Picture 1: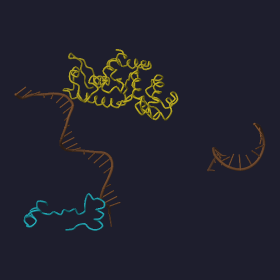
Picture 2: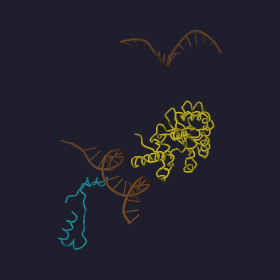
Picture 3: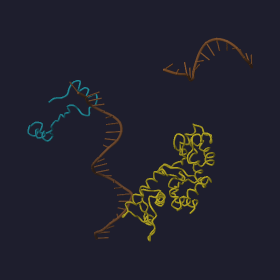
Length: 48
Length: 220
DNA sequence: CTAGTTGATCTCATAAGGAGAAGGAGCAGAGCGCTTGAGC
């Protein structure tokens, strides 16, 4: 995807931004979900 | 109906121990009119009895006609036991020995206080420190009673409370015998008997007599 | 100590930003002393 980078993100960091321009979550899976695809897409549906 | 008698009864009602013997027992001019039917004369008796030096009528701020009464001797005896041991205890004693027995006006002018009583412009803060000189305006100030804050807060709270329940009462009437018989509400602590006298004087209720005692109603 | 004089000194006179922080509004509900108030 697209993630803010560079001077804009550096400013966004120095002045705490209550509303990040591109907020994101890096989600890692625990069980079979991490290996197989059906369960992982299921978790995606559960989260989106 | 004697104003000397009238003021005495109210004095007895006062919850003396409730205020830890610090505030002198205040009685209102509103409840004075309750005992004495002819108000026209009640002011006249208290007027000469003011300059007679046996009463102090202090102006309060809960309404425009707020005039409280403090016993002179008790007003004296209580200020020393409150002022002494404090930085302001200095010239308040002078105020007592000079101003009180030489004047009876409810508010003192700037030129009056400074010249007639020989007061400087530095010690005047000490009287403002603990309820001795209020603030009427730039030029004048009403006489204060120390520790009057708590009283009026409970007094105003009580007046509202009694008024509210009277209105709530079915058909908007409530027999006077039904106040004394019923336990006083905990919201008002100055005494249910104390307040019912106040609305009578304030004419928020009328003492309507009937076969079943006397009744109070909101004005129509 | 007293007048007289000399300057100072004054007075009066005629005409196609933003991000954030701070205040206040309005509604929304919880709680509670109260005032009944009526079923067993």
